[PDB]
Amino acid sequence: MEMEKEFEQIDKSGSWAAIYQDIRHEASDFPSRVAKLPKNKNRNRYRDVSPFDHSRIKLHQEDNDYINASLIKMEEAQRSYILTQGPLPNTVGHFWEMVWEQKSRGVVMLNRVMEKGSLKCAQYWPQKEEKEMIFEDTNLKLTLISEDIKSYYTVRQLELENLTTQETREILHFHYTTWPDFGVPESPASFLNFLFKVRESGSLSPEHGPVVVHCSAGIGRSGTFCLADTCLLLMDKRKDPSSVDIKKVLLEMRKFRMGLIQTADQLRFSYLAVIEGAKFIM
Ligand SMILES: COC(=O)c1ccccc1Oc1ccc(N)cc1
């Protein structure tokens, strides 16, 4: 079926939970043996969210190459993404090592450091220009260059220096600051505006490594971001845009990381975002 009318048909019939459970039943199951090794317990935020072995990002290190991060490669859309958990106190240096080694231009952050009164991720970037951060375990230096605070999101320019080679690179930090502590946003307008700002920066384009996107577990809000982006790109590429099937795209993405889209409300919000976004594109 088309999207917008399939949408009204699920709303009128109140069957979002049944649609979402079908997706959960059909989703791929691949091994995640490296994630579950005992030496990696303090590298995982949640025991039930792990990268598959076949798509996990490897650190260029011979001691321990593990990070909780997955490469999502979308062949028809010609777009790749790295989805990862919010960094932990003992993985902030690994996080920036990955950004460096994978040649990423942008980092997309969809959570606040504290939500619901608890810490959802480490403070992994500097907050003042004159107070830079040094990650001694991976030999990197990170400096805040500039910050632009807007009503729904903040953009930061950062400098990452590989202290071993003295090479430097400019990284863009796109921080969506207004996702509510409970539920999903009422309108997708500010989320789409944010997606378009990431696109306009070059961070999603083939001349760079894949964008790094995270929330707390790296599957829920993060899944919504890449699912909406890929669906909108396919609608632009194809002769028949009404042939884009959001459930099929989601199942394809779940071949590369488990659990993408965590609730039936997030599924409904993804439909809403693609539907409204397709009108603005034209
Ligand atoms: C302080 O950060 C910035 O504002 C910034 C600085 C340097 C390069 C890029 C930047 O972000 C963007 C600007 C404009 C659009 N449309 C998207 C992204």
Image (cartoon, helix red, strand yellow):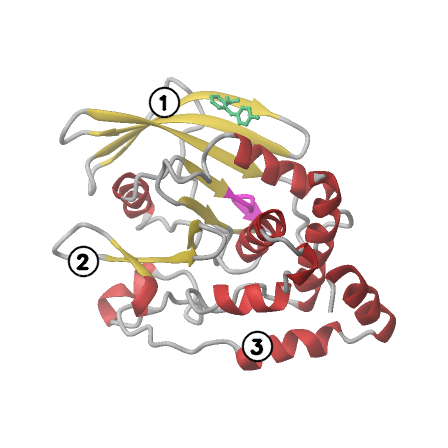
- For the question of whether residue 234 can be seen, the reply is yes
- Quadrant into which the C terminus falls: top right
Horizontal placement of 99 versus 121: left or right?
left
For marks 3 and 1, the one nearer the N-term is 3
User: SS at mark 3?
Assistant: helix
Query: Is residue 211 inside the magenta stretch?
Result: no
Using the numbered discs, state the Cα–Cα distance from disc 3 to disc 2 in whole angstroms.
32 Å
Using the image, determine if residue 5 lies above or below residue 213.
below
**Residue on which the image places disc 1:** 131
Outermost residue to the right: 12
Q: Position of residue 207 (x, y in %)?
A: 37, 36
Mark sitting on residue 108: none
Disc 1 residue lies near ligand 1 with CB under 8 A: no
* Residue type highlighted by circle 1: Lys
Q: Position of residue 213 (x, y in %)?
A: 46, 47
Q: At 54% from the left edge and 57% from the top edge, which residue is drawn?
A: 223
Outermost residue to the bottom: 25
For marks 3 and 2, the one nearer the N-term is 3
**Residue on which the image places disc 2:** 64
Q: At 70% from the left edge and 57% from the top edge, which residue is drawn?
A: 269
Q: At 52% from the left edge and 35% from the top edge, which residue is drawn?
A: 174
Q: At 56% from the left edge and 44% from the top edge, which residue is drawn?
A: 112
* Residue type highlighted by circle 3: Arg
User: SS at mark 2?
Assistant: loop
Nearer mark to the viewer, of 2 and 1: 2
Location of residue 69 (image quadrant): bottom left
